[PDB]
Image (cartoon, rainbow, N blue to C red):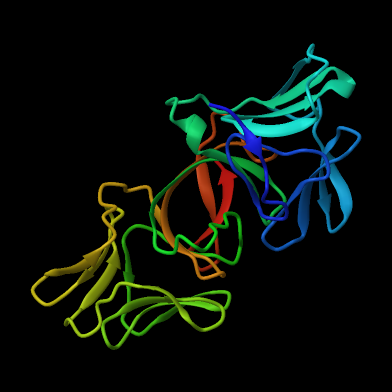
Amino acid sequence: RTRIPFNGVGTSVLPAYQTLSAGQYLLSPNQRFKLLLQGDGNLVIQDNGATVWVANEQQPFSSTIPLRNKKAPLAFYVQYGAFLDDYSRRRVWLTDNSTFTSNDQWNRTHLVLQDDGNIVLVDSLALWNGTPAIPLVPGAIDSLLLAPGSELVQGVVYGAGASKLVFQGDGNLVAYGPNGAATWNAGTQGKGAVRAVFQGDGNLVVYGAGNAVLWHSHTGGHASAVLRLQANGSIAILDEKPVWARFGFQPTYRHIRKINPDQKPIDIWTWH
C-alpha cells in the first residue's frame, strides 16, 4: 500500500497513508492549537499562535534514526506509527507506539489534534455512520458522547453545540444540524415506538410495543463502542482506542476518556 497527498488542511485529523508536506497544518476543533510542518523541517505545535512543542529527540516514547536517502522530500505521515522524514538533518523521527495487535491496524490508525493540545494516534473504526456526507471530527470538547447502556429518554433534548439528538413525541429518533434542519432520522414516527436505547452491546435500537424492533444500527456485539453526536450534525457509532500521544500516554497505562463533572465522557483521551 502507498501514500497519497494530504488535502485536509485545517481539519483536526491526518488519515493513514497521507503525506503532509511543508506549509500544511492541522487545527484542533476549537481552533486554539495548530500542528504545522515548517519549511525549515521542524514539526511544531502552536498555541494561539505561539510555538509550545517541537518534534525531537527529547520527546518521550519517540526514536530518531538516520535518513540516508538524499532524495527523500520533507514529509510527515502515519503508517501505524508516525514518521517525519527530514533529510536536512539526516533524520527520521518516529513514534514508539503501543504493541500492535493486528496488521489491520495499519489501515485504521490516524492522527488527531485534540482540543487540549495533545496529538494522539487513534486506532479508529466507524461501525455505523448515519451521515456519510458530514465529516467525522474527533477531539472536540463540543461533541456529545453516549456510553453503551444509555437510555434516550423520550422528549429530552441531548445537545452538542447547536446540534441535537431527540427521541421525539411522535416516536421518531432524529438528529438535527446547526442550521436547525434534520441531518438523519430513523423513520420511526407513527409506528408506536416506546423506547430508544444505545444498548450495553453497542447496538442503537428503537423498540415498539411488545419489545418489537422498529429500527437498529446493526452494531450489536461491540461493548466498547460509543455513540457520538458532533456539533456539525454528524451522528455515528465508533470503536476506538489510542496507541500513542505526546503527553499523558505511557505504553503500559490503561487508556480512558476524560469526564465532565456530570460523569459524562468527553471525546478527549487521557491515561491511567
What percent of the width, then of the height, locates residue 187?
28, 76
Residue ID at (56%, 70%): 231
Which residue occupies the extreme bottom position in the image? 169
Left or right: residue 21 compared with residue 136: right
Residue ID at (29%, 52%): 219
Residue ID at (68%, 57%): 115
Residue ID at (51%, 84%): 180
Quadrant in the picture for residue 96: top right
Q: Is residue 257 visible?
A: yes
Quadrant in the picture for residue 78: top right
Quadrant in the picture for residue 175: bottom left
The one of 271 and 142 positioned closer to us in this rendering: 142
Left or right: residue 37 compared with residue 129: right
What percent of the width, then of the height, locates residue 63?
72, 21
Q: On screen, 255 above or below 210? A: above
Q: Is residue 227 visible?
A: no
The one of 13 and 271 positioned closer to us in this rendering: 13
Q: On screen, 248 above or below 48? A: above
What percent of the width, then of the height, locates residue 247?
69, 40
What percent of the width, then of the height, locates residue 102?
42, 26
The quadrant of the image that shows the C terminus is: top right
The one of 231 and 4 positioned closer to us in this rendering: 4
Q: On screen, 113 above or below 181? A: above
Number of dots carrying numbers: 0
